[PDB]
């Protein structure tokens, strides 16, 4: 009722308010715009609700910022601006919270959910009926597609679309939404009527205001500017004011006007610089106009000035002509209404995000109904046509029916104007005219003329932001609405020509057109396409696109030919026009319901009219003389558009094949007749060579020739679809098939001519075009041309010699063949042999492949055979990976991925990868080698002998028969047509026999073998064809009259030097085969020219290698020359550590070895009472997928401390000896910083150095025996060092002092600690050495034989350990021991300095304290055991939980049993009164197992210490380590658990067993490191446990639970799939495309020095080293279903399983701190830029 | 002279153990010059092909690699038309430990697979990349010529 | 299965390499024994080079075979 | 004897140079025809630098051949 009038009065009075009345500065636009947005939102939300009380059902009643009411009181409370500008009201409409889970429940209706940036798209390659059907996260059910190819793609900025759940037509198989797997106020009539009223009024206001917005129209803006100029110089302002008032927006609810402004519009004419210059020239008063104004233009439009007085603004308005920017003059009220409509559209978009499902399903339906209802109010609303008629009568022709649409203006009475419709009459469909087929133009059309049509027609008046908003709000809503989808399709089709003409000719920014979205979301649907085809609207679309194309046509050779655009197109609209039109045609054809529809007379003639303009449009001429200065670029557009047409033809073929119903043969015959007649209408020069032989005159080397000929391709297709006899019948009676096949043969000849490099004088562009013509991605052009030539030969049963003369003429070989010119001086010059090779290949191809003439059971089998042949001819050269195989095979073959995979599986056998970074390869089956013909078309890229020899090697039973076997030509007549059996006619003709004879004779005379093998294979194929046709022992009579057997005999009885063995062996095989067929008629020919004694001896020569004598003489020569060399050597001799620069100098300068000194993330405390930590025994490396990656807070803090705290640093080096002077020269010359550099041998990163002294065991009796049994004083081993020298001693002092000063690997804490001197460095060096030993043990844990794992395969690690030990010993001996006065790491009662403090004390006692090792180990082990037993027994949370903990441990593994003596010992050490069970052996057993497992790392590290001690004292290089007369490896290989512990105690401790050790008294020593011994990690230390399949991290990210990083954990972080995964800690890192791609995870919340991140999307793991900014990418340890790794694995969405060995290699790379070294080595020369 | 002792223990290494298919010997008047032999490997196109080499040694052999030239006709992409196989990484700042036997074995290895990047005989490289007929035939005829070239120095 | 390997100077390297082992792992063993980076090593057997992706059995390697190391000649 | 030399921009120059000539002579011809400084340019044949001392026949360059010229 009054609601409509109230809405109209309010909306049509925005400028009437005093707040907006006066123009304001740019900073006051922002707050005014915010006020307008809030006012419009509030008012429309109040009205859309019933009287303004239904809001709480939509928005939150009590949001934040409450304390000014949440909702407006009444209509006046929402319309006022005093409250809004006072910032009193609150934005109640905002729903930006964490409760928005986009929960949408739909049944049948399309999801229609627009995709935000970063959201995945699940394009299933098998369920989807096309390549456009995607799915959203909430609509994707992974259960539906076990074992499918699901290509997951990440949504980007330019990728806009909707989900398609519930669309039964879009999916080949029914799918279940994930949601379905798990009082109404908006459904009453009153509310739906009210929302309909509001939406209708909104759209009517929008259309009314923009219908009068003709100012920014591209067609009119120019003369608006011109006329305004004219009235400003001729000084007649009255009519200027009249014009301005006429153009001003008008409504029914001095002399110069006021409240005016100047608005510029965005375009692609200019970049930022030119626009900024134009703005600066426009108005200098605008502050920062080159800065603030320019970026606003980047999003829609902007206003540069505004004032009441028009005189000032108009002077600056004329900046239009400065740079051509489409700037218009507009009134303030008009701008206000335009901004109002922009905010209205924003409000309509916002309304679609309301979570209320009922509100959405009502709002969308009513909005669609208003959009699709007929647009009334056309009469009442102001008609804008009279203004343009009156002011621009010159450009407005009265009689022209297209006077309106040529100006982008509606018709009189506000109706859609008349489009350039062109319906063709049936009387003009009989034949295909050389020019455009005759059509009629109707002068009347009855459009629906609805609101949606007006909005789409006004698409050239909007700005970028408003445009994009309008498409985003209209296209998805209507397209997804299953009720209004067909209506939307009809409405946009009826106005299709207007849209296309607008985007082509009249549009400022064509690339933002709505037609692309319309076609994508509408025409890609079987029902819409079926409805379009049922009418003639498809013909209208085709003819609109043809009319777009025909404006650039040209006349060449009696036909209409498309041309490259040369007119000024700075807007580039024509390229978008062509691309969009061709895509529309291809899309509409792809979804045709009835395959006969495109072939119907009107449809076929229209499609052929479209495709004719590009038939031979591109011509090239063989440049001769001077090479082309600049490569031609014109061919690119022709390539693009002809590729589009080729795709059109291929899509037509695909839809013909896939549709079950066949096609009426009459339609095929009619199409053949039409195309053949049109192509025969060509004009060709003729010539005669003999009296009665007439051929076409055309010199390819001189005249223009075309590669791509789509019409011949269509003709070949159509002839193939029907019988040969029917195809001949459909041919026009007065026609010459040579006229239509000569162009295809010209293309073939041109390709073979450029293949041999004849056209090198042209640029590389012609070679690119030629390679494109070969193996064309969309279609087989070359094979179709060969087929056309085969048809031309087969259909000339009257004048067969004429064909051969013509065929050989185009190759320009006729001058040589007839004897006109000599062989050497042909036009090809020296390249004649290669051309003849190609010619023989061409003839063999004509003869051999009869595929197009075969009849298969089904088209599926035909496609399967094509795929198999392509795979076979691509594989036999060498086994290849899946990615390379897909790259080689033509694109149109690989699209059906399932068929391609089936064919590949049937053809080849999978070869598993062997290495750790190689792809799985496919090897062609041996039995299929017999089916490879190395001369057929598929092997065109390769040479002939190479393929021949490869097939022979794969076919020879041994290396003896590499060149003694012949290749049978692949010629057969199986399943062949009756009329196709006579392809051998032109080969068996006399003229071709003479051609072969002349070729063989010239080959003998000039002695060139370049084309000889091909010629012999061709002769063999000719004989095989003749045998297949006639039958047994048949020979062509043509080669008998002309004695070719003499030439073959001359080939055979050569000197074995002119021709190779393969030529000789093949020729004799041909002779024997034909001689055996008939010897009598053939032996006469030989004696006719070669005499009798040759023939008689030939039989004696037969039945009895030649090179055996040659090999024997070569061997004898070898023996002679080697004897000579030995004699020379004898007479000559009768006559008579490694540095980097000072080779053989034997200098005493110390060899400093580069090393890496940095922290490690492998140190972590292990909480006691943890069954997962100490119970499970380790059988080497493993991976548990069932447990999700997770980290504990204490462990995370441990990694952070390891990154920060310097007490966990470790030395790792490459052991490459280098002089100190040479190292200094390397530093100075290469300018690396001394702090960090790269080793000059392995290029590995290094930061710290440590010299090695000249160790020696001479004149001493040291061994491990007195190391175990007597003191291990560091001097008692330093006695090994040789005596020094004063110069050497001071040099040592200097080098150690400079290393101490210049190396930052030393902890700053101990550097700044009190009483720190140069004598204290030994303690921290020993600490780092113990840390390195701990690293070695942790790494050794990963091996299967953990007892002796650390001994094997650590030779370089042992060398590093020996180097470090020698260096620290040299430092101590030279400088002096500090007497342990200063403690680098005080035993603080709150912090843990080192996680291996037990072994730290062991090292400190062994090296420094002059006491026996066997007693120090016992002391340390006893103290740690006492501490651990006290902690475990006196621990809590077990007294009533010992039973469940024991049960859990037994579930994990097996708990050892404690004997009665061990029971007594453990009770004596400590006993508990909490034992409440009958038998308390459970807690004792648990304590036993826990103590053993906790102690085992210390024991193994002690064994490693003993090992390095032996290596330091080894007598010989190969000396097995022996302890107490027993070999450690022999005595520890098969020792497990308690037995291993006891044997180790016997080996390393002065005691005899664990019981004996426990019996020892409680000796107490106050060493700093024995108080409150920390407990370290017991179990295997490695990276996180990745899932079995990488698809889980992509497909099922919602299902998988993973720990997340709070850094930037907002903005739909719960559904985006841009994240990485940290393998060190399991914390998933989200990539928000900001702040260095989120590299911050290293600087905090994880280990800092380095880390490895996994990217599931690309299936590659990245390694980061933080000291430089460097990082690398390597293949993730995931192996694809088809053997592939890297990014190629995840593409095409194949199942990606886990390879354990590769992941173990990654773990071993990470643990040993080789990751920085690996990263440094990968770059090589690139790493230099870092330093 | 350090270079003389270098060549002396190189000769000792050769006399003790010579890599298969490779042999060399210096000259009495000038030990600096050498005469070297190379046999084409078994599966290569150069099968049983024996090719002479000539090595004129610069005085600073540790600093500068010897100047090497073939004494027989060679058709290889990495071998110049003058027979002067070029070495340019042996003179780098940090060269690996090398002797004459090492470089001879490197040449023998190169005889199987050429290095298409940075070629010496451009026509040989283009012939190897495609149109292998003339390449294999020329290799065979060069083997024949090397066999026929009986030397009597 | 045991093979011998001679370095550039002539020092013999003793290795025990499984018949199915890859050439990349062989070069890893070489650098383990000596320290020359695997990417800096090319192996030649009977004068022909060896590629990383094929095993020792596929190259006809018998017991106590001799594999050589060669230079680069990238020039 | 024509060989095509491709410059940095993309333009190609044909030279009627005899095989007996030197690489430095080829550079001199290129300079004479285009006024380019031969010192800056470094004629490289399919990835191999060309020495001014050697001749075209030494590299065995003949008939059509593309010689990229990098300054
Ligand atoms: Zn599926
Ligand atoms: Zn759904
Ligand atoms: Zn969905
Ligand atoms: Zn030195
Ligand atoms: Zn190194
Ligand atoms: Zn992390
Ligand atoms: Zn697959």
Image (spheres, coloured by chain):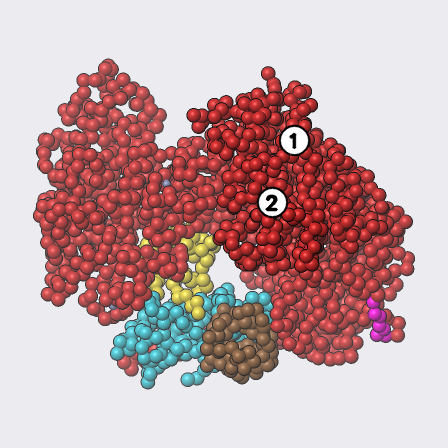
Chain colours: A red, B cyan, C yellow, D brown
Quadrant position of the N terminus of chain A in the picture: top right
- Badge 2 crowding class, 10 Å Cα cut-off, few under 14, some 14 to 19, many 20 or more, is some
A1377 on left or right of A1169: left
Q: Nearer the viewer, mark 1 or mark 2?
A: 2
Task: Judge whether residue A289 is colored magenta.
Answer: no
| B63 and A1233: which is toward the camera | A1233
Give residue A450's position: percent from left, percent from top: 74, 36
Name the quadrant containing residue A76.
top right
Query: Is the same chain shared between marks 1 and 2?
Result: yes
Quadrant hosting ligand 6:
top left
C59 on left or right of A941: left
Residue bearing mark 2: A259
Residue bearing mark 1: A9
Q: How far apart in space, not on screen, are marks 1 and 2 (Cα)?
A: 21 Å
Give residue A500's position: percent from left, percent from top: 72, 48
Badge 2 marks a residue whose secondary structure is loop
- What chain does mark 2 sit on? A
Magenta residues span A684-690
Task: Judge whether residue A687 is colored magenta.
Answer: yes
């Amino acid at each position: 009722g009054s609601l409509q009038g109230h809405i109209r009065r309010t909306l049509r009075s925005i400028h009437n308010l005093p707040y907006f009345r006066y123009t304001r500065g740019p900073t006051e636009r922002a707050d005014m715009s915010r006020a307008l947005k809030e006012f419009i939102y509030r008012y429309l939300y109040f009205v859309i609700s019933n009287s303004g009380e239904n809001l709480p059902t939509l928005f939150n009643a009590h949001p934040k910022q409450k304390l000014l009411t949440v909702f407006p009181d009444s209509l006046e409370d929402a319309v006022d601006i005093d409250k809004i500008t006072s910032q009193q009201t609150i934005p109640f409409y905002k729903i930006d919270e964490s409760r928005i889970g986009d929960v949408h429940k739909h049944t049948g209706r399309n999801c229609g959910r627009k995709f935000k940036i970063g959201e995945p798209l699940y394009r299933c390659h098998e369920c989807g009926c096309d390549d456009t059907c995607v799915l959203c996260i909430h609509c994707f059910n992974p259960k539906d597609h076990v074992n499918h190819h699901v290509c997951t793609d990440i949504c980007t900025e330019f990728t806009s679309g909707i989900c398609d759940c519930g669309d039964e037509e879009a999916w080949n198989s029914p799918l279940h939404c994930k949601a379905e797997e798990q009082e109404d106020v908006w459904n009453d009539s009153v509310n739906i009527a009210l929302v309909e009223l509001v939406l209708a009024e909104v759209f009517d206001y929008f259309i009314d205001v923009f219908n009068q917005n003709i100012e920014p129209l591209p067609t009119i803006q120019k003369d608006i500017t011109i006329k305004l100029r004219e009235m400003t110089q001729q000084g007649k302002m009255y009519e200027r004011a009249q014009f301005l008032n006429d153009l001003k927006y008008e409504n029914d609810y001095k002399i110069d006007p006021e409240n005016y402004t100047v608005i510029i519009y965005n375009d692609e004419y200019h970049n930022y610089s030119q626009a900024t210059t134009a703005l600066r020239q426009g108005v200098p008063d605008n502050v920062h106009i080159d800065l603030l104004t320019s970026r606003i233009d980047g999003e829609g439009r902007a206003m540069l000035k505004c004032s009441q007085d028009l005189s000032s603004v108009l002077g600056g308005f004329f900046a239009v002509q400065t740079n051509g920017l489409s700037a218009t003059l507009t009134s303030w009220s008009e701008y206000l209404h335009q901004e109002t409509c922009k905010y209205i559209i924003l409000w309509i978009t916002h309304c679609l995000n309301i979570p209320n499902s009922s509100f959405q399903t009502t709002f969308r339906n009513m909005m669609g109904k208003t959009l699709c209802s007929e647009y009334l109010n056309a009469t009442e609303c102001r008609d804008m046509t009279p203004v343009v008629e009156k002011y621009f009568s010159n450009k407005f022709d009265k009689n022209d029916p297209y006077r309106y649409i040529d100006l982008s203006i509606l018709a009189d009475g506000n109706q859609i104007p008349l489009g350039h419709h062109k319906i063709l009459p049936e009387s003009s469909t009989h034949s295909l005219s050389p020019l455009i087929n005759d059509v009629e133009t109707p002068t009347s059309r009855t459009y629906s003329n609805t609101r949606l049509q007006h909005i789409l027609y006004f698409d050239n008046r909007y700005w970028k932001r408003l445009r994009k908003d309008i498409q985003n709000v209209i296209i998805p809503t209507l397209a997804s609405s299953n009720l209004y989808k067909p209506i939307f399709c009809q409405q946009v089709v009826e106005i299709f020509n207007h849209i296309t003409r607008s985007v082509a000719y009249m549009d400022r920014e064509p690339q933002l057109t709505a037609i692309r979205e319309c076609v994508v979301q509408l025409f890609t649907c079987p029902t819409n396409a079926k409805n379009i085809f049922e009418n003639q609207s498809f013909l209208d679309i085709v003819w609109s696109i043809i009319d777009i194309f025909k404006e650039f046509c040209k006349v060449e050779g009696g036909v209409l030919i498309w041309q490259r655009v040369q007119k000024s197109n700075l807007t580039k609209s024509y390229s978008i026009s062509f691309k969009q039109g061709l895509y529309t045609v291809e899309t509409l054809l792809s979804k045709v319901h009835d395959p006969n529809i495109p072939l119907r007379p009107k449809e076929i003639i229209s499609l052929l009219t479209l495709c004719k303009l590009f038939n031979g449009a591109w011509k090239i001429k063989r440049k001769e003389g001077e090479h082309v200065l600049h490569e031609d670029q014109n061919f690119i557009s022709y390539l693009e558009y002809t590729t589009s047409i080729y795709s059109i033809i291929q899509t037509a073929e695909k839809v013909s094949e896939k549709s079950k119903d066949s096609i009426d043969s009459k339609l095929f015959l009619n199409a053949i007749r039409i195309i053949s007649s049109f192509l025969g209408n060509r004009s060709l020069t003729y010539k005669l060579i003999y009296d009665s032989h007439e051929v076409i005159k055309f010199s390819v080397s001189h005249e223009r020739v075309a590669f791509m000929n789509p019409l011949q391709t269509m003709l070949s297709f159509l002839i193939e679809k029907v019988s040969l006899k029917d195809a001949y019948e459909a041919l026009e009676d007065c026609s010459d098939f040579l006229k239509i096949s000569d162009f295809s043969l010209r293309s073939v000849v041109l390709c073979s001519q450029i293949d041999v490099g004849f056209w090198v004088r042209n640029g590389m562009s012609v070679l690119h075009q030629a390679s494109y013509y070969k193996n064309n991605p969309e279609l087989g052009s070359y094979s179709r041309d060969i087929h056309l030539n085969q048809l031309a030969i087969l259909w000339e049963r009257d004048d067969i010699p004429r064909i051969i003369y013509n065929i050989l003429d185009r190759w320009e070989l006729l001058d040589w063949f007839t004897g006109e010119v000599d062989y050497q001086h042909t036009v090809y010059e020296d390249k004649i042999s290669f051309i003849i090779q190609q010619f023989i290949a061409f003839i063999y191809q004509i003869l051999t492949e009869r595929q197009y003439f075969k009849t298969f059971s089904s088209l599926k089998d035909r496609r399967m055979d094509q795929i198999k042949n392509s795979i076979i001819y691509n594989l036999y050269m060498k086994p290849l990976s899946y990615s390379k195989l897909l790259r080689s095979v033509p694109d149109y073959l690989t699209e059906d991925t399932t068929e391609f995979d089936e064919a590949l599986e049937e053809v080849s056998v999978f070869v598993e990868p062997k290495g750790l970074a190689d792809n799985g390869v496919f090897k062609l089956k041996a039995s299929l080698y017999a089916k490879v013909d190395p001369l057929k078309l598929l092997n065109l890229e390769n040479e002939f002998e190479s393929s021949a020899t490869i097939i022979k090697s794969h076919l020879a039973k041994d290396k003896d028969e590499i060149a003694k076997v012949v290749l049978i030509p692949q010629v057969s007549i199986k399943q062949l047509d009756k009329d196709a059996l006579n392809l051998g006619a032109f080969t068996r003709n006399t003229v071709f026999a003479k051609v072969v004879y002349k070729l063989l004779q010239v080959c003998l005379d000039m002695e060139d073998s370049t084309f000889l093998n091909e010629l012999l294979h061709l002769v063999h194929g000719i004989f095989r064809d003749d045998e297949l046709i006639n039958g047994k022992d048949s020979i062509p009579e043509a080669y008998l009259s002309k004695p070719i057997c003499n030439l073959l005999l001359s080939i055979a009885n050569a000197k074995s030097d002119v021709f190779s063995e393969s030529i000789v062996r093949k020729a004799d095989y041909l002779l024997e085969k034909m001689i055996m067929k008939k010897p009598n008629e053939l032996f006469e020919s030989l004696i006719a020219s070669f005499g009798n004694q040759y023939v008689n001896d030939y039989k004696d020569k037969k039945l009895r290698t030649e090179k055996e004598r040659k090999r024997r003489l070569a061997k004898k020569h070898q023996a002679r020359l080697l004897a000579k060399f030995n004699n020379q050597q004898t007479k000559f001799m009768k006559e008579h550590f490694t540095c980097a620069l000072c080779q053989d100098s034997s200098s005493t300068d110390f060899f400093v070895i580069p090393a890496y000194h940095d922290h490690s993330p492998i140190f972590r405390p292990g909480n006691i009472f943890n069954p997962n930590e100490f119970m499970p025994m380790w059988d080497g490396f493993y991976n548990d997928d069932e447990k999700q990656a997770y980290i504990d807070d204490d462990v995370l803090e441990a990694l952070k401390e390891n990154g920060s705290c310097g007490s966990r640093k470790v030395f790792v080096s490459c052991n490459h000896h280098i002089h100190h002077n040479c190292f200094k020269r390397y530093v100075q010359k290469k300018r690396f910083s001394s702090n960090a550099f790269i080793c000059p041998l392995c290029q590995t990163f290094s930061n710290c150095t440590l010299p090695l002294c000249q160790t020696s065991k001479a004149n001493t009796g040291l061994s491990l025996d007195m190391f175990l049994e007597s003191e291990l004083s560091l001097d008692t081993l330093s006695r090994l060092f040789k005596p020094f020298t004063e110069e050497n001693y001071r040099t040592i002092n200097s080098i150690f002092s400079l290393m101490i000063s210049q190396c930052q690997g030393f902890d700053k804490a101990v550097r700044k600690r009190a009483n720190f001197s140069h004598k204290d460095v030994s303690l921290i060096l020993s600490v780092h050495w113990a840390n390195t030993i701990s690293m070695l043990e942790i790494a050794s844990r990963l091996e299967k034989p953990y007892s002796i794992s650390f001994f094997r395969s650590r030779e370089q690690k042992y060398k590093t350990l020996k180097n470090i030990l020698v260096c620290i010993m040299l430092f101590t001996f030279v400088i002096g021991k500090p007497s342990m006065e200063f403690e680098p790491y005080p035993q603080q009662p709150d912090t843990v300095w080192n996680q291996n403090q037990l072994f730290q004390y062991i090292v400190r006692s062994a090296l420094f304290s002059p006491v026996s090792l066997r007693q120090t180990v016992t002391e340390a082990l006893t103290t740690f055991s006492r501490q651990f037993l006290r902690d475990f027994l006196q621990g809590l949370s077990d007294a009533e939980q010992v039973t469940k903990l024991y049960a859990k441990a037994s579930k994990i593994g097996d708990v050892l049993k404690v004997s009665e003596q061990m029971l007594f010992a453990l009770r004596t050490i400590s006993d508990v009164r909490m034992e409440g069970l009958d038998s308390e052996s459970i807690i004792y057993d648990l304590a036993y197992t826990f103590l053993l497992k906790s102690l085992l790392p210390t024991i193994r590290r002690c064994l490693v210490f003993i090992k390095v001690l032996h290596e330091l004292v080894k007598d010989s290089e190969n000396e097995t380590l022996v302890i107490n007369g027993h070999e450690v490896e022999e005595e520890l290989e098969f020792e497990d658990t308690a037995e291993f512990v006891n044997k180790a105690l016997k080996m390393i401790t002065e005691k005899e067993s664990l019981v004996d050790l426990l019996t020892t008294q409680e000796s107490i020593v106050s060493h700093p490191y024995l108080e409150n011994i920390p407990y370290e990690y017991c179990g295997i230390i490695k990276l996180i446990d990745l899932s079995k399949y990488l698809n889980t991290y992509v497909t099922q990210s919602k299902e998988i639970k993973l720990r997340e990083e709070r850094s930037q954990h907002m903005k739909n972080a719960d559904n985006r799939l841009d994240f990485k995964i940290c393998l060190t800690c399991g914390v998933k890192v989200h990539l928000r495309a900001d702040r260095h791609e989120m590299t911050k995870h290293l600087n905090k919340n994880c280990f800092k020095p380095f880390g490895a991140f996994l990217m599931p999307n690309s299936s590659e793991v990245c390694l980061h080293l933080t000291q430089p900014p460097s990082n690398i990418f390597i293949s993730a340890p995931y192996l694809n279903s088809h053997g592939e790794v890297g990014r190629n694995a995840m593409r095409r969405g194949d199942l990606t399983t886990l390879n354990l060995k590769r992941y173990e290699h990654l773990n071993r790379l990470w643990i040993n701190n080789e990751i920085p070294g690996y990263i440094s080595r990968v770059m090589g020369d690139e790493f230099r830029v870092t330093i | 002279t350090p270079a003389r002792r270098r060549l002396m223990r190189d000769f000792k290494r050769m006399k003790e153990d010579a890599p298969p298919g490779v042999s060399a010997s210096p000259l009495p008047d000038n030990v600096m010059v050498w005469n070297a032999m190379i046999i084409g490997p078994a599966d290569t196109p150069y099968e049983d092909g024996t090719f002479r080499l000539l090595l004129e040694f610069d005085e600073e052999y540790p600093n500068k690699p010897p100047h090497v030239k073939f004494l027989s006709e060679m058709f290889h992409p990495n071998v110049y038309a003058n027979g002067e196989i070029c070495l340019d990484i042996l003179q780098n700042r940090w060269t690996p430990t090398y002797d004459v036997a090492s470089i001879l074995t490197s040449i023998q290895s190169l005889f199987n697979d050429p290095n298409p990047a940075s070629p010496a005989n451009v026509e040989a490289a283009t012939l190897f990349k495609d149109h292998k007929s003339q390449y294999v035939k020329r290799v065979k005829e060069t083997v024949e010529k090397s066999w026929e070239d009986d030397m009597d120095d | 299965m045991q093979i011998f390997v001679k370095t550039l100077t002539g020092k013999t390297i003793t290795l025990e390499v499984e018949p199915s082992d890859t050439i990349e792992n062989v070069k890893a063993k070489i650098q383990d024994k000596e320290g020359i980076p695997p990417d800096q090593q090319r192996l030649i057997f009977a004068g022909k080079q060896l590629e990383d992706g094929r095993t020792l059995s596929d190259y006809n390697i018998q017991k106590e075979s001799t594999l050589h190391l060669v230079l680069r000649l990238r020039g």
